[PDB]
Amino acid sequence: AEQATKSVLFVCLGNICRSPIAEAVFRKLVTDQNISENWVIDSGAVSDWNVGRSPDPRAVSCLRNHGIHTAHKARQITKEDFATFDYILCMDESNLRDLNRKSNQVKTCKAKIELLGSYDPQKQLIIEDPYYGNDSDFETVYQQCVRCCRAFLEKAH
């Protein structure tokens, strides 16, 4: 008794730490709920810094600690992303400014652009960049992503 097909693009600065973790977490959630076939899921970066790279090894390891694997390779957000995804969910205030600016530069913007943390029941609005941190920072990002992803899934139609 089908749920309509929906799409989400997680966005961070580099697409190596936060948005690959958010994507993988969301993918695991929808697979646990047997509705993976009803979602199109991707991640992408504001910048072109890391294009082609697999996620930061700390992020891959964080995900493996929680039984999750990812085959993502970094890519930059494109004009076409704004036209094709239903939701673009980003990590911090800087990502939000940059995506709202990019969306102004395109003619077709279907995507609703939001902070992923706006979905957190625990009200942690910002998912802070762990790149210069340690494994515990990646774990904090993981746990934030779990909360936000879970809430988003139950609100999004």
Image (cartoon, rainbow, N blue to C red):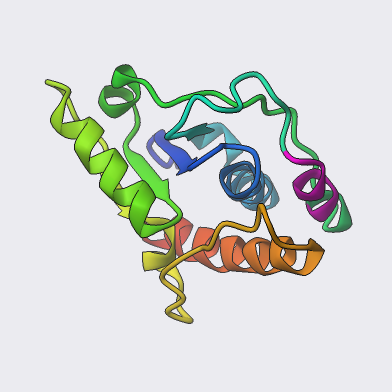
Residue drawn where x is 58% and y is 67% of the image: 144
As for residue 117 lying within the magenta part, the answer is: no
Q: Estimate the x, y position of residue 74 in percent, counting from the top left.
A: 61, 27
Residue drawn where x is 58% and y is 60% of the image: 145
Residue 68 vs 84, above or below: the answer is: below
Q: In screen coordinates, is 21 left or right of 1?
A: right
Q: In screen coordinates, is 59 left or right of 39?
A: right
**Number of marks drawn:** 0
Residue drawn where x is 34% and y is 42% of the image: 87
Q: Estimate the x, y position of residue 3 in percent, counting from the top left.
A: 42, 42
- Residue range in magenta is 56-62
Q: In screen coordinates, is 5 left or right of 111?
A: right
Residue 96 vs 11, above or below: the answer is: below
As for residue 57 lying within the magenta part, the answer is: yes
Q: Estimate the x, y position of residue 154 in percent, counting from the top left.
A: 44, 61
Residue 41 in sight in this render: no
In this rendered view, identify the residue nearer to me: 66 or 39.
66
Pick the quarter of the image with the N terminus: top left
In this rendered view, identify the residue nearer to me: 70 or 139.
139
Magenta stretch: helix, strand or loop mostly? helix
The residue sitting at the bottom extreme is: 122
In this rendered view, identify the residue nearer to me: 10 or 38.
10
In this rendered view, identify the residue nearer to me: 103 or 86.
103
Q: Estimate the x, y position of residue 124 in percent, counting from the top left.
A: 46, 76
Residue 27 in sight in this render: yes
